[PDB]
Amino acid sequence: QGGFSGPSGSVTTVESAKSLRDDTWVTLRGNIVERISDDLYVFKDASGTINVDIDHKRWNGVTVTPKDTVEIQGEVDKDWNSVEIDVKQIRKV
Image (cartoon, rainbow, N blue to C red; front, side, top):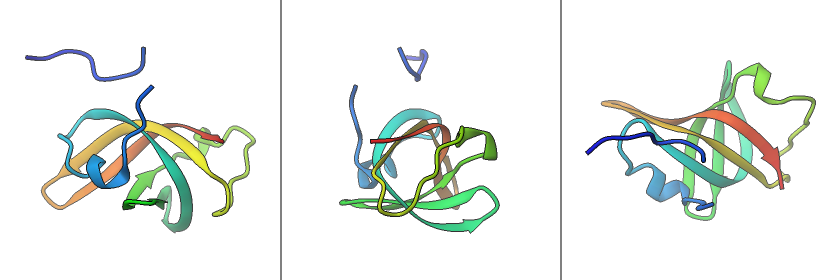
């Protein structure tokens, strides 16, 4: 009961992503609405909000504001005290 969780079409809701197991690959769509600290941002979709970690290298020349719909792909990082998405890719849509 193991395998690769990663890219090879489904967009998951923020609220349900919070329920997934640690180390699960997800794609979400929504808006980045606030920067909370170094590399930590708040991502919101119609179902809820979740914190996302976006390293400086993920932007790739793209400027994103809260009005931009963006698609993010990365891993659910869940610990005893937190759930966040470690973002591998962000693109505007």
